[PDB]
Length: 48
DNA sequence: CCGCTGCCGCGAATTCCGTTTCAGGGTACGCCTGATAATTTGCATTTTAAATACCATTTATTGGTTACT
Image (cartoon, chains in turn purple, green):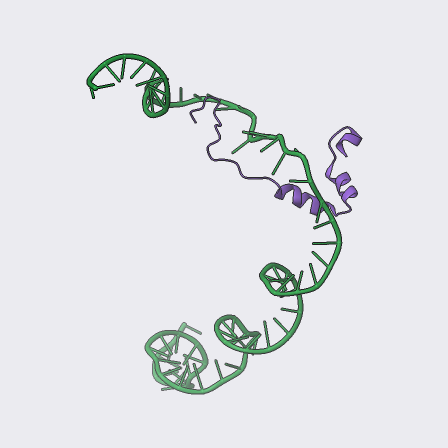
C-alpha cells in the first residue's frame, strides 16, 4: 500500500484495506514493539 | 638433545556536562475445542423515617400573700 500511494498509510486507510475496525488496528500497532536493552549507550560517548 | 621464537592474554586519569528515549528481520492458511474473561443474581451487615425502655441531677412553675403607694 505504501508503494502504491507513494507514502506511508494512515491507520484509517489501513483499517479500510484489512476490513477491520480502527481500534483493533491501533491496538495491534501498539502491541507490536519489542523491549529495549538496558545497556544501550544513551550518551554519545560510550560511558553512560 | 632444556635453547629460541610465536602465539594468546592483559592493561591504558578524574569529576561534571550534552544528547537524537531513536530506528533496523521481509515468512500462510483455515478448523475444532477448551479456557478464561467477561457478564448476569441473592445474602450477608450496616444503617433504619426513627420507635423504642430506664436511669439521671437541675430549672420551671410555684402555694400562694402580709404589709402598705
